Image (spheres, rainbow, N blue to C red):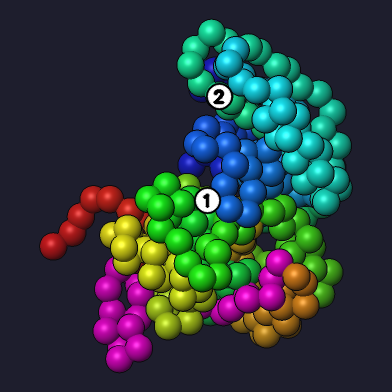
Amino acid sequence: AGGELDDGATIPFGDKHIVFTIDGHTVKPLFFPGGDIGRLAVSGTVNDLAVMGAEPIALANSMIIGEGLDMEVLKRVLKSMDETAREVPVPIVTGDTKVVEDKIEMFVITAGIGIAEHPVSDAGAKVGDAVLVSGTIGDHGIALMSHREGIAFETELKSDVAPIWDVVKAVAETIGWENIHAMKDPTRAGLSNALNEIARKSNVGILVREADIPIRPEVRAASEMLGISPYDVANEGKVVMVVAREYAEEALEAMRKTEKGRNAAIIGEVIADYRGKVLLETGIGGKRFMEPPEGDPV
């Protein structure tokens, strides 16, 4: 229907499925530990396509730049975008650039198209499935917030920004797309939002063992100083994947064999009770609902 969840849309095309997504990027500063707005723009789009089971086919880039922006800054961002797309690889086939008088530096908006031979969505989780994350959680958002507050560590806290279509493909090549039941790119509102979307869209409950969520020591420390949970901030180089129970170990091992999935872990399982909710277990057995950041409860 003409005219006007926001993770990407699927469009049937004859026998196959085209996935279409768009995302704007307004990160400030433009460069951060581990990356920059250019790498972020390419990685986020690629990751949004990957979690829908779509091989990236093309990216389109719109840049809005302020008149006062130094040409060298622009060149560095373009070089990063080009390099990041080449890691996939996926061509940047078209774009647009606008200059404004406004006192901004640069915004980058990327759209992407992918083709999914075997579509995956956040609505396909099944009871008994294992819930995996491809690596440490909270790195991107905590690294950027930390830098902004002048918080620094011996081992520099960096963003994990990177395209992870390779991590997703590694699992599919091992266990088959049919055994990957759901995925989500844990960007806005982080891991907690991602898990709640899968629980609600698949109409299943999710039980997560808190101790099993991989969190770097530096991220745990910084998040305590910042007063925010690492489960609630953006990740930019991770995937949440729900897989058939009998293939959980194989999927875990496939991810761990990739450089970007080295720290992958099984963090929970899909259940038949509290459908639509995510329950978090403490080491001692304590349980509470894992709610996306903001409202509630008591």
Q: Residue at x 40, y 78 (%)?
A: 210
Q: Residue furthest left?
A: 298
Q: Residue furthest top?
A: 101
Q: Residues within 10 Å of mark 2 (few under 14, many from 20)?
A: many
Residue type at numbered disc 1? Thr
Quarter-wise, where is residue 172 in the image?
bottom right
Secondary structure beneath disc 2?
A: loop
Q: Residue furthest bottom?
A: 284
Relative side of 79 to 66, left or right: right
Q: Which residue is mark 1?
A: 187
Quarter-wise, where is residue 167 in the image?
bottom right
Relative side of 164 to 87, left or right: left
Q: CA distance from mark 1 to mark 2?
A: 23 Å
Residue type at numbered disc 2? Glu
Q: Which residue is mark 2?
A: 105
Q: Residues within 10 Å of mark 1 (few under 14, many from 20)?
A: many
Whether residue 26 is visible, yes or no, is: yes
> Which residue occupies the foreground of this view, 174 or 16?
174
Query: Residue 5: x percent and y percent?
Result: 48, 42
Query: Residue 39: x percent and y percent?
Result: 69, 44
Which image quarter is the N terminus in?
top right
Residue 265 on the magenta segment: yes
Which segment did they paint magenta?
260-289
